[PDB]
Amino acid sequence: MLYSDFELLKIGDTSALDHIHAKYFRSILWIGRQWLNDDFLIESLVQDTFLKLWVNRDKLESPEHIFYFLRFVMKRECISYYRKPKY
DNA sequence: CTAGCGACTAATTTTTCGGTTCACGGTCCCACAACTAACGAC
């Protein structure tokens, strides 16, 4: 049975994350490049966004919701770096 | 040789910034990898 990637993420199978990563990696990279200008920090934030999606995988309800989550989170990460004294 | 004589120091409190968390609609040159057309063997 070929379940959709939403149910693979819900099950607890790590290859699901490979699927969502390979699908939305470049979109999240573009989202980050829109808000910042440091590719290093953008890549770090993309990794954090996907890992935090995996951690909060017990909070998704819709197949599209996953995508929304990613975009949302990634944006706010960029936003937080406007306030960090270190950065 | 000797004697008379002319107010600072210690204890307690209070407050601004950072951390954390939540998280949907040009050029020229020298090598290196393909690569293919022809050539030779089973």
Image (tube, rainbow, N blue to C red):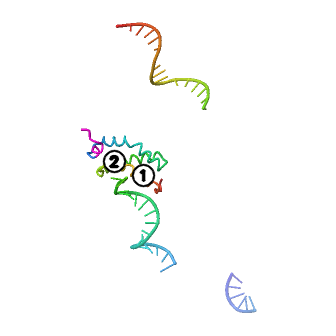
Residue B10 image position (x, y, % from top left): 42, 72
Q: Nearer the viewer, residue B33 or B3?
A: B33
The chain holding disc 2 is A
Query: Residue A3: which quarter of the image?
Result: top left
- Looking at numbered disc 2 in the image, what kind of residue is underneath it? Glu
Q: Which residue is found at the position 37% from the left and 41% from the top?
A: A23
Position of the N terminus of chain A, as image quadrant, is top left
Mark 2 neighbour class, 10 Å CA radius: few under 14, some 14 to 19, many 20 or more: few
Q: Is residue A8 magenta?
A: yes
- Looking at numbered disc 1 in the image, what kind of residue is underneath it? Lys
User: Disc 1, disc 2: CB below 8 Å?
Assistant: no
Residue A37 image position (x, y, % from top left): 49, 48
Q: Which residues are magenta?
A: A1-9
Do the residues indicated by labels 1 and 2 lie within the same chain of the protein? yes
Residue A56 image position (x, y, % from top left): 31, 51
Q: Which mark is residue A75?
A: 1
Disc 2 designates what residue? A64
Q: Nearer the viewer, residue A65 or A76?
A: A65
- Using the numbered discs, state the Cα–Cα distance from disc 1 to disc 2 in whole angstroms: 17 Å
